[PDB]
Length: 315
Image 1: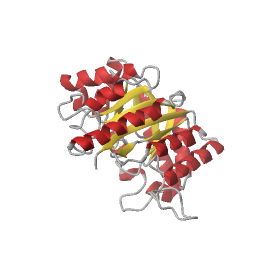
Image 2: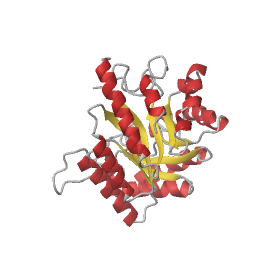
Image 3: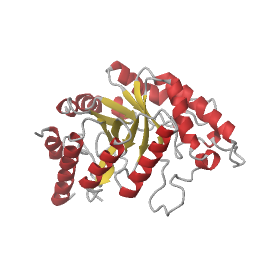
């Protein structure tokens, strides 16, 4: 078990689909290896509430019950995002954005509904996902993505999402989650956002590095640097959706093993702040990226690659 080999460092997590927790083959692996679960899709805004007031709890209830049942705590993925979210939250179906008052009321009601239903099992939440702009942000352009949320409320909508989550479960750790988390320009922006949040008194406990890396990746030097930067502003860091894609050869196979091995070194050296490393999907078979891309430490048949033994046993 990976969770065991890293007992003294951080939890080892995985994001699951409906089958991953219903099939005894897949369940065996999940239960062996991981001590943290995220719903891959069952807890996002559109899946759980595609029309105002019309909830669909069925899929998430299964994964949560799986987690209650086997004594694993969940990361709640996510409360707010520009994708997989019902239009109704920010616009009126003519296609006109709502006012900041209605938008806020929608975000509040949704967050109360979901946080309240799973707070017994969920230990932390990705409260806002992917609000920072992608690189190249010229001097004086906005550092935030220009989503409908941002168009209605500016940066404030982020502060609110966090206030509402905190009021709904004051004991949950609250994370800002984003991708290209080790890129030099974007991490600076992610740092800057979280710094403004704290200076406004927003209750943010942590940063989530998605860690969708590749094999030319970002370099381990950039990761190390990025974890050091985020450490100067929060007490808590998670890798939330770790993946090392190739874009199989035995030299590629090699490249990707080295990469995993060296990454987990860096993480190990930062155990103090790193609480959890979660993998997106259990195996290459389930991977959002596909079997070709050969991400993740288990293969199309849910079997440990050699790279799994490299990361499991270290120093």
